[PDB]
Amino acid sequence: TNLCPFDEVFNATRFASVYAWNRKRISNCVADYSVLYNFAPFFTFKCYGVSPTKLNDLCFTNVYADSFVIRGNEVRQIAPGQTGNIADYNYKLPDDFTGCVIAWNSNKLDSKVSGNYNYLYRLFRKSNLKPFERDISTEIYQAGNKPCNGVAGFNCYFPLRSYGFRPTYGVGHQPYRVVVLSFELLHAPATVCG
Amino acid sequence: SIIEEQAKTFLDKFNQEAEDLSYQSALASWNYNTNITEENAQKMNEAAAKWSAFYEEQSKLAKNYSLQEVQNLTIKRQLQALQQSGSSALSADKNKQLNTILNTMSTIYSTGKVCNPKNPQECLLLEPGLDDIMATSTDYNERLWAWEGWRAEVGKQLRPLYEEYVVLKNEMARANNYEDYGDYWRGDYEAEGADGYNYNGNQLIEDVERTFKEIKPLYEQLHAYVRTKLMNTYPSYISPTGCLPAHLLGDMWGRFWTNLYPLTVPFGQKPNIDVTDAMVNQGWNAERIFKEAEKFFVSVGLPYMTQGFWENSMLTDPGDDRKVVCHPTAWDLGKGDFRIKMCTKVTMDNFLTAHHEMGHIQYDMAYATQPFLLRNGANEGFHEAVGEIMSLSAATPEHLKSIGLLPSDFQEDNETEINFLLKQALTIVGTLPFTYMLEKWRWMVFKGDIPKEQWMEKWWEMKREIVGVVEPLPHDETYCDPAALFHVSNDYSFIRYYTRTIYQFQFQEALCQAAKHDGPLHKCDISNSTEAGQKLLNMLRLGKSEPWTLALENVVGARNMDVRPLLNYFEPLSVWLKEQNKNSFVGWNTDWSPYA
Ligand SMILES: *[C@@H]1O[C@H](CO)[C@@H](O[C@@H]2O[C@H](CO)[C@@H](O)[C@H](O)[C@H]2NC(C)=O)[C@H](O)[C@H]1NC(C)=O
Ligand SMILES: *[C@@H]1O[C@H](CO)[C@@H](O)[C@H](O)[C@H]1NC(C)=O
Ligand SMILES: *[C@@H]1O[C@H](CO)[C@@H](O)[C@H](O)[C@H]1NC(C)=O
Ligand SMILES: [Zn+2]
């Protein structure tokens, strides 16, 4: 018929970092939510606002897909009303969320001996995140009263740190690929159905 | 509260970069100890050097924060742990002098040899040698010459090195607000918190004395029984009233009395329980032992073992062109990686070492969620007590017959219980005075109460006043008997063994009472008991986050060390010994020596 590009989101060869997460829009695009199944290693598939079974009859205006890779013991922070390092400085969800999240293990594809330093995450920031926005800045974090002049030193830090994924790590430390889907209904006609 | 935020921000960075460095160092060290080769050693050295340099730089940088301005105790403990790095608070020349003194002293300890007075071309080492003579031989003169030799060709060489080493250690200690290299060691036993939970290093010297004073009478009964039993072997050298010669204790230093068992069996007509033929005839391998240990641990509510544990661990000798170090160790590489290295054979002792080296992984796994500088034990002698309560539980006839290694109609007699209790006593209660005396003497010599002139006259008189052991030959002021021991000549504290032997029985009594067990405490099994596991897990979740007083209260409901469980454990043995020691002298005098 027309199908809809979920194979370029879930089966992408390379994912993004947490602080630079990709965001994709779904056009006039008949989409089915059963191709997502049959992929057994879904360690997490739980939905908010909508029921997974009756997701093949509702129609929406557009759908947003956000993809990134985080640590295993950080998946629980991708949820409304959660506090933590990831959901204060990297990715924040609103309390009125009307979509759901998918997570699965990616040890074989993202962990290598001697470390995989290509994935980064924010560690220091002044304020919170104001749900659904990104920050890409390499400015030096200032903690003390003395001003920093673009050089790292005492009480002046670089705000980006790298993951060190290795295949020998424990279950809570392998990389996990996360895809978040969001459904909204605007004034325009609903153009995505099952 | 402006410094608290700065401390938190600094500690976050320190944690993130220490995790990676520590993991790399641990991985290199593990790879060396299974694949011994030169390049593995080179990689291990390069991995350790970077971590050491990073730690030193971080501690020097963290010195810039004041502990008085920090109100949260959780981060205050981390700051105290990080800034406490007063091993390099010395000039460079003094540090290199200390390092060379340590290296040469260890070299003399390892290389030293003794020679037979009647066979000059025969000379022996310590490990493949004299230890066998002192553990097996019976001849008086042979043990005498071995003892005197080792003393002569160890102390004569290690005396001036120790004399020059003490002052350097004191100078190092008097740079971290410590008055000697004593309380510096006693500082591990320090706590801070709410009212009634504090504990400093000056309270340890009083608790130890109270504990020993309570312990003494049982040791006197055991000493009298051993002395009256060790006279059919040497019926011309042991005095009925006097002390015991040092070269007849089944060990070179008298640290343990466990080799005197064949000469001191209460009932020698019936053997002890040994399930080794049964395991062979039933087809047991190395993996079955660890499966049984895991099942025992999960029966009380503790978690399973990780998937990586079964695939990354070396549970058997490789048996090929790959030389390994054969010594049981549990490892924490970090970041959820737990492994065990052990040579496993089908024997009871391996079956118990398995259950001891997994109670270390279950503690490590327990506190994996704490920050980096809080992931340890509580009081230096807490990690070896949680490992020796599991071996105690999984050695009971009831437990052995519940897994199919004893017949279902097996009946336990009363003589084997006495044999087991006496064998346990020869190892547990027979070493406490040794530890107490050695620590007391070394604390005094660091404090300055014993000058160099009275260096050896005080040692050999505390020997016959506390332990009850007399030297066979006179010793001048040139010998250094204490230096002829591994821990004294390698800078290892010798107080954890006393505290562990006190804590293990408190833990066992609390868990047994939680499991609703009736009968003697030495026949207690905590299997199939969720309450005991819940209590123990409540204790093992903290690490160094809270003062060890809270950790101890979380199990035993007591704030400090106690002796009653230990004395309760040896009650049938005590009554049997009192019945046996009915027409004999119990104590000893200090005015007899086998050379006057
Ligand atoms: C701990 O409990 C388990 C099960 O609750 C016991 O295992 C059973 O023990 C009975 C003996 O009364 C046997 O007849 C069963 O065949 C056993 N079942 C299994 C699956 O092993 C176990 O013996 C208990 N352990 C102790 C020390 O009491
Ligand atoms: C031991 O090290 C050598 C070289 O260092 C290597 O070739 C060999 O594969 C290692 N052994 C194992 C079991 O990996
Ligand atoms: C500690 O002293 C001051 C601040 O107290 C600081 O400038 C200095 O760099 C610190 N020392 C080191 C060795 O970093
Ligand atoms: Zn141990």
Image (cartoon, rainbow, N blue to C red):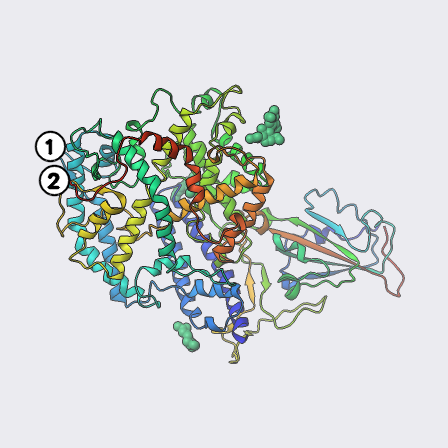
Q: Are marks 1 and 2 on the same chain?
A: yes
Quarter placement of the N terminus of chain B: bottom right
Q: Viewer-nearest of labels 1 and 2?
A: 2
Q: Which mark is residue B595?
A: 2
Pinpoint residue A162: horizontal percent, then vertical percent.
Answer: 55, 60
User: Callout 1, which amino acid?
Assistant: Asn
The answer to whether residue B329 of the structure is visible from this angle is no
Q: Residue B156, relative to residue B68: is it above or below?
A: above
Ligand 4 within 8 Å, label 1 CB: no
Which residue lies at the image location 54% right of the left edge and 38% below the top edge?
B297
Q: Is residue B134 left or right of residue A190?
A: left
Q: Check disc 2: other Cα within 10 Å, few if <14, some if 14-19, many if 20+.
A: few
Q: Earlier in the sequence, mark 1 or mark 2?
A: 1
**Picture quadrant where residue B265 is located:** top left
Near-viewer residue (B555 or B573)? B573
SS category of the residue bearing label 1: loop
Q: Is residue B575 left or right of residue B139?
A: right
